[PDB]
Image (cartoon, rainbow, N blue to C red):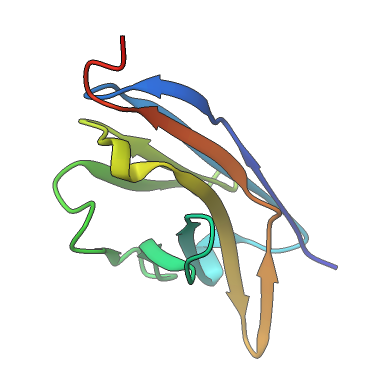
Length: 119
C-alpha cells in the first residue's frame, strides 16, 4: 500500500541545524496532507509542521520561525529543515500521511540536540 520512511537524524549541538526528509511510496504527497510529529520519551506525540495538498504549510508555535517544511512534488519527498536548534527539540521525529480515511506512519528517526555548552 503506502510506505513512509524518514531519513536524517542523529546528534547536533545546540544552535545548530539538521535536515530531515520523508520519502513516500504508493501515494503522492502533493495529493494529500502530510504531518511531521515528534515525541519525547514519556510524552504524547506533538505535531511539528503540516502541509496540505494545495501546499498550505502550518507550524507549531514551538518551531515557527526556525523549522521549514518543504515538498518537492517531482521527487515525492518532503523535507524538514531545522535551523537554530534547541536542546528541547530532542525527540523522535515521525512522518505521517493522511490519504482519505487512511492514516500512514513512518517509524521515526531520533534527533538529539545536546545541551548548551555541553562540553
